[PDB]
């Protein structure tokens, strides 16, 4: 029937035309949007003659301005804000802000000045400012894609994209300001109201967006196993933010949406990953639909009613205007360069040329031009506006967008760096070799012997897409430095791929490594890393002040807070109503409520005095509460009989003020969260640097040739590691609870990661069904998300709980009581020596608080902190101290004398014997470096080695005093203590040593003073006899 929704046809047709254009013009330089404009023009000239087609284009080609703005702009702005890398955007926030705001102002003003003078149109400054704002908006989606692919600079892409976003947002604000002056003029008003309006649009808008964003990310972090709710909440939050901002609050909706998108992007962790990957594509699709629709409408309407009033002189104006805007953008960038080169990422002239030439115009400008076209009606201003906007869009998409690819080549930015070319060539060669191996495997298959191999080998091909003298010693120094930095980069990437680093920490470490590589003689400086864990002083100061500020039934204060929350609505409503109506009976009804609240507060007084008596008035909070109570009594009495300023105005304020007693704790939580978000990054960066240094120091050991170069590199590595360890140890002292929270979160994250890996292994091997594995995965996922809601500060466990959790005491209640009954807590001051080299191994130390320096043979200078234990080797092997222990802070330490430990060893024996557990804990630590040195030239990290060893066990060596080695079942064999010799060659192995694969059979002897111990790891599956 005639009532059908004909716009559906136009929307679907726009989708089909977009698909066709993106398919045909994929490899050509001309972007598909120009083809969409041409198709829209063809459709418009057809509709002008075929009446049937008009009906199917009328309802959308003549859409109302407000519908256009409210439906499309939220999509485009939110997609732009949500797609980009916010952290890099914030790391270059000053450059982007200076340009997108001040440069936008100057560019739009200069464009307006040009329009008022060059054009024969007698435009006033308001219309000229509308013209300038429309044409200062930018849409660099193509240029940013080219930069991202070619990798000239990842930061340049973010700078250009963020400038486009903030320029788009502020170009809509300016157009809104000047649209009212041109099409909705009003009586002139005061500078006071102008300032109020400026605040409303520029300051309140971002705050409204921030509030909605925080509420949204709050609710998102509590939604579990419900993707649809997350997606719908994102959609509704965006659209309601824009709508409530523009229509109800009259704040700048576009800026609110910008802030909302940026915040929701930064807080991505509150969104389940499978919903994040969906949302990215969802908003990309919505933006694509919006762009296609806008271009089709522009073509249709510009051919229908714009080009019918275009004069021969306008084209000259269009060309001059294109040149003018290009020159203006270049001049703005050059003029501000003296400032921008000194902040953020800096600038270089080639980057300036790229940023100037890449200023493509797009959908936002055309949407605003359509708004002007619709609002102007019969005035030629609308036709001229749309003509010039479309002309500039076409020229930039035909000239700039096509030549940008070649300009990157001319400016020397499209070149692929040699490291990337070598890596890609190696990867391609490896892929080809693997394909050859698979082909040889298949050619032996009986069921594939008749395959047409000429087609198969051709189809699967993957091709390269990029197709002691003084000088000599310094050259070797540079070689070693560069190769060390390369190894460190590889190590950081490997750490990230296993979840041991956050992407931010990985980025920091890699960026520092690359910065060092280009500069002369630079190794990664710890002083530059130090910025990652420097807590800004504002937050500790706020925490201390608030804790001072805040510092009997549990339900009472909650009840009173609820009472005040119930107060505020009646109290605020009553008096605005009383003023607005001037019924009196309604006024009386609300007035009566004061007595109810006064009764509640009298009950408060009675029941608080019940537990405090005269001491009630000591606390300042109680003093203020008493003041408000007495003032309420005064208000009632003066109500029975200058009236307003006491009765009515104080109720509004004194109520809402006394709520802060509950707010202060939540601000403490917020400050704790802010400190945590920095301390976690600091720990991640420091630990990543430590682990990378440990690995690379065992790569370089036989990868740089000359010994002196190796010694310099090792010295630098050690002097970095020690500083990082000391700094991270002192961080724990400054903020103990936040450090405990960080470390517990890391522990849970690692446990869940490995549990997920076991679930996937069980699924792949078929021991668990394809359905139930998903159920366990869902449980793991919901457990992972609840970490984001974990408290930012966890009170540090008391010392007895640290003793309860030592590795070799866990779960053995009787031994836990035995040690707890005999361990004595010794307190030591700064600079004291707990034990010294050569001292008899008189006992163990478990550090419950503080930091200690280990020094000994100057070769070994490590530090240890809370939770670490000292002296296990001494107590087990009865040999003097290996290092001197010095207190770098006030230190508490559980001391267990060696005699009590020997008694415990004697008295506690089972299959997991206490001596066995101690020796196992020592053996893993001894073996980890030993296995590292052999496999550092292969693809396993430190955590892989430690997990590989955890599967192992310690040989009894008394049930069989000789060890027979079987390659088919043993991955590695390590001698931890004592001496061993091969039964065949009688060659003695006299140190911590990996038993060489060539050895068949080890043998030993009974020498009590040096009784040997041996460690072994069986292959993934050796169902044979275990002999722990």
Image (tube, helix red, strand yellow):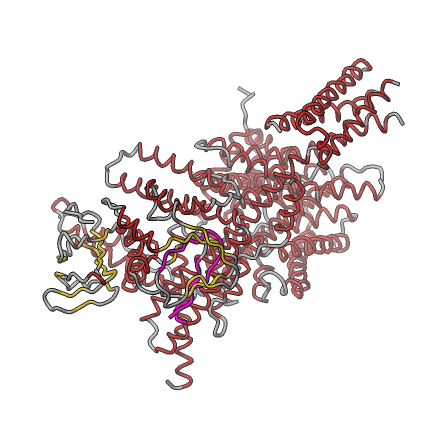
**Snapshot quadrant of residue 860:** bottom left
Q: Is residue 146 visible?
A: no
Query: How far from the left and from the top, in percent, is residue 552?
Result: 62, 29
Residue furthest out toward the left:
984
**Snapshot quadrant of residue 764:** top left
Q: Look at the picture and state if 409 lies above or below 33.
A: below
Query: How far from the left and from the top, in percent, is residue 140?
Result: 56, 52
Q: Residue at x 45, y 56 (%)?
A: 865
Q: Residue at x 33, y 54 (%)?
A: 899
Between residue 259 and residue 998, name the one nearer to us. 998
**Snapshot quadrant of residue 1004:** bottom left
Q: Is residue 34 magenta?
A: no
Residue furthest out toward the right:
642
Residue furthest out toward the bottom:
469
Between residue 888 and residue 307, name the one nearer to us. 888
Query: How far from the left and from the top, in percent, is residue 610?
Result: 67, 25
Q: Residue at x 77, y 52 (%)?
A: 116
Lateral position of residue 427 relative to residue 603, left or right:
left
Query: How far from the left and from the top, in percent, is residue 362?
Result: 59, 47
**Count of marks overlaid on the render:** 0
Chain part drawn in magenta: 842-864
Lateral position of residue 806 relative to residue 414, left or right:
left
Between residue 47 and residue 582, name the one nearer to us. 582
Q: Is residue 71 visible?
A: yes
């Amino acid at each position: 029937h005639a009532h059908a929704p004909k716009v559906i046809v136009f929307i679907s047709g726009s989708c089909l035309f977009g698909a066709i254009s993106r398919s045909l013009f994929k490899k050509l330089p001309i972007p598909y949007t120009v083809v969409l404009l041409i198709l829209g023009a063809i459709l418009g000239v057809v509709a002008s003659n075929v009446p049937l087609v008009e009906e199917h284009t009328r309802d959308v080609a003549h859409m109302d301005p407000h519908v256009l703005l409210q439906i499309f702009l939220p999509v485009l702005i939110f997609e732009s804000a949500f797609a980009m890398d916010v952290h890099t955007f914030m790391r270059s926030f000053s450059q982007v802000c200076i340009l997108a705001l001040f440069g936008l102002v100057v560019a739009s003003v200069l464009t307006a000045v040009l329009a008022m003078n060059l054009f024969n149109y007698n435009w006033n400054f308001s219309e000229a400012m509308m013209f300038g704002a429309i044409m200062s908006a930018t849409d660099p989606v193509a240029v940013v894609a080219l930069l991202k692919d070619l990798g000239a600079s990842k930061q340049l892409g973010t700078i250009i994209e963020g400038e486009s976003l903030l320029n788009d947002g502020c170009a809509i604000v300016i157009f809104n300001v000047f649209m009212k002056m041109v099409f909705f003029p009003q009586l002139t008003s005061t500078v006071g109201q102008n300032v109020l309006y400026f605040l409303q649009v520029a300051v309140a808008g971002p705050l409204w967006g921030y509030a909605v964003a925080k509420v949204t990310v709050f609710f998102l972090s509590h939604i579990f196993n419900d993707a649809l709710v997350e997606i719908t909440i994102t959609l509704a939050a965006t659209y309601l933010t824009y709508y409530i901002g523009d229509i109800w609050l009259e704040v700048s909706g576009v800026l609110a949406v910008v802030v909302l998108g940026l915040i929701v992007n930064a807080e991505k962790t509150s969104i389940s990953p499978e919903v994040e990957v969906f949302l990215h594509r969802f908003w990309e699709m919505l933006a694509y639909l919006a762009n296609t629709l806008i271009f089709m409408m522009v073509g249709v309407v510009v051919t229908q009613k714009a080009l019918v009033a275009v004069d021969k002189m306008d084209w000259f104006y269009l060309i001059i205007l294109y040149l003018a805007i290009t020159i203006i953008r270049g001049m703005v960038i050059s003029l501000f360069s003296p400032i921008l080169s000194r902040i953020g990422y800096g600038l270089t002239w080639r980057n300036a040329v790229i940023m100037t030439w890449g200023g493509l115009r797009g959908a936002v400008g055309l949407a605003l031009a359509l708004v002007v076209e619709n609002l102007a009606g019969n005035d030629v201003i609308g036709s001229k506006f749309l003509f010039h906007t479309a002309g500039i869009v076409v020229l930039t998409l035909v000239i700039n967008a096509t030549t940008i690819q070649t300009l990157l080549r001319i400016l020397g930015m499209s070149d692929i760096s040699i490291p990337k070319r070598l890596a890609m060539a190696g990867a391609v060669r490896r892929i080809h070799e693997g394909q050859n191996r698979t082909l040889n495997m298949l050619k032996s298959d009986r069921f594939l012997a008749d395959a047409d191999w000429d087609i198969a080998t051709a189809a699967c091909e993957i091709s390269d897409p990029y197709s002691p003298s003084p000088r000599e010693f310094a050259d070797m120094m540079e070689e070693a430095r560069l190769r060390m930095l390369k190894a460190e980069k590889i190590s950081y990437w490997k750490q990230f791929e296993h979840g041991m680093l956050a992407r931010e920490a990985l980025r920091l470490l890699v960026q520092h490594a690359e910065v060092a590589a280009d500069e002369k003689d630079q190794f990664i400086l710890v002083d530059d890393l130090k910025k990652s864990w420097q807590i800004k002083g504002i937050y500790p100061w706020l925490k201390r002040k608030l804790e001072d500020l805040i510092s009997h039934h549990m339900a009472f204060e909650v009840t009173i807070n609820i009472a005040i929350v119930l107060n505020i609505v009646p109290i605020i409503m009553e008096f605005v109503v009383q003023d607005k109506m001037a019924l009196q009976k309604i006024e009386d009804a609300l007035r009566i409520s004061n007595y109810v609240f006064f009764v509640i507060y009298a009950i408060e007084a009675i029941v608080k005095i019940l537990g405090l008596g005269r001491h009630y008035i000591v606390s300042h909070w109680n003093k203020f509460d008493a003041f408000i109570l007495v003032v309420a009594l005064v208000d009632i009495i003066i109500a029975e009989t200058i009236k307003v300023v006491k009765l009515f105005r104080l109720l509004r304020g004194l109520r809402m003020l006394r709520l802060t007693k509950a707010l202060i704790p939540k601000l403490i939580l917020v400050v704790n969260g802010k400190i945590n978000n920095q301390l976690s990054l600091g720990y991640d960066v420091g630990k990543g640097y430590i682990i990378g240094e440990e690995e690379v120091g065992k790569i370089i050991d036989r990868m740089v040739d000359n010994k002196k170069i190796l010694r310099e590199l090792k010295h630098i590595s050690e002097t970095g590691r020690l500083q990082v360890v000391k700094e991270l140890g002192l961080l724990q002292r400054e903020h103990p609870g936040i450090a405990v929270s960080v470390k517990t979160r890391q522990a849970i994250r690692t446990i869940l990661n490995h549990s997920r890996e076991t679930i996937h292994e069980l699924q792949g091997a078929g021991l668990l069904d394809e359905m139930e594995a998903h159920k366990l995965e869902l449980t793991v996922e919901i457990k992972m998300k609840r970490l984001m809601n974990a408290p930012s500060s966890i009170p540090p466990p008391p010392p007895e709980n640290l003793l309860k959790n030592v590795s070799w005491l866990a779960g053995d209640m009787k031994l836990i009581d035995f040690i707890k009954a005999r361990a004595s807590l010794l307190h030591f001051d700064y600079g004291e020596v707990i034990v010294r080299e050569g001292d008899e191994s008189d006992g163990l130390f478990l550090i419950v608080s503080g930091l200690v320096k280990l020094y000994g043979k100057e070769v070994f200078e490590d530090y240890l902190t809370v939770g670490n234990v000292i002296g296990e080797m001494g107590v087990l092997t009865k040999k003097p101290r290996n290092a001197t222990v010095t207190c770098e802070t006030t230190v508490q330490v559980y001391f267990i004398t060696a005699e009590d430990m020997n008694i415990a060893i004697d008295t506690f024996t089972l299959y997991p014997s206490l001596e066995y557990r101690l020796w196992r804990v020592v053996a893993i630590r001894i073996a980890t470096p030993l296995i590292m040195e052999q496999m550092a030239f292969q693809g396993w990290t430190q955590e892989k080695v430690k997990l590989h060893l955890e599967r192992g066990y310690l040989v009894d060596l008394a049930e069989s005093h000789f060890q027979f080695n079987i390659d088919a079942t043993l991955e590695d064999v390590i001698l931890i203590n004592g001496t061993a010799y091969n039964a065949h060659t009688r060659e003695e192995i006299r140190s911590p040593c990996l038993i060489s694969r060539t050895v068949h059979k080890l043998t030993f002897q009974y020498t009590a003073t040096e009784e040997p111990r041996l460690f072994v790891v069986r292959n993934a599956e050796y169902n044979g006899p275990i002999l722990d």
